[PDB]
Length: 300
Ligand SMILES: Nc1ncnc2c1ncn2[C@@H]1O[C@H](COP(=O)(O)OP(=O)(O)O)[C@@H](O)[C@H]1O
Image (cartoon, rainbow, N blue to C red; front, side):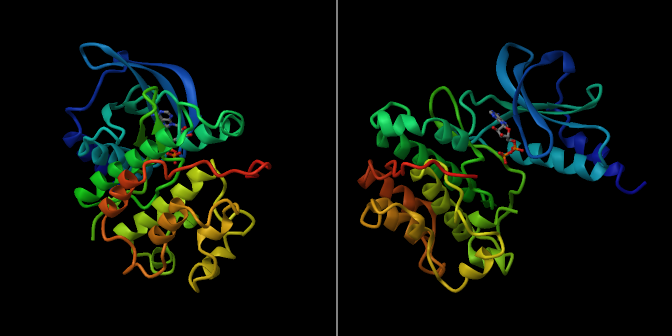
């Protein structure tokens, strides 16, 4: 064998993180993740219990899949930040599958969050969940969490409202690192220098961050809604219609419209050199993130 040894040498380094299956119990079906279902329950860190969600993949798939499964956890262990989801352990060979244990975010992801609290914005626009005081702090938490990733020479390459989870504290954190690589497909969240060229940088992550901001101020619309995935690879290269054109007419004079337009510029020499240029903006204008909606909900 030549691919069945990679698994058993990898778990040697991740051996201090193994937990017996008698310390993990499954209660809920939290959601349908990318590769398998995620379950919700409680895990005991040999001392006390904590509410936890688990990513699970059965032991029937190829070893090629199990290596990527454990590589997500190995990368996740190198992180510690109040705006990044932190794992607490793994579990090797429990009965039918392999377990990935990561803390529970009570209020789910951000896209389903906004999609469910849409009419609440049209009827109660000053609510503790969805007011510019909270939306700006949320986008700010995502920003400094991505700045923490970039600080330690990491590129996420997949910034969207699907990979940002919110907890009962209503603080948001970075969620999915399935596509995260080292420092030097979601095409709608990718700058053109990363689409036709396959090169990723901090500026490509800033492009996806600006797309996330458009996704937030619209409460979850599908970027470039109405254009197929084949029409967008040709339209974004020749600088026609930045994402700002897809906004309601209530924008195009605001501070958030310009911001996502500077974060999403074809000339990456004009894009911010670091996430801290964007973060320092979110302090001079603390009510920039506003809900800009229509009377017709978005159609996925
Ligand atoms: N720790 C968690 N807390 C709450 N929900 C989660 C958690 N982990 C995963 N999920 C749910 O499972 C899916 C995320 O799994 P993943 O494969 O990481 O997909 P994504 O690309 O959305 O991050 C989402 O639907 C999300 O709502």
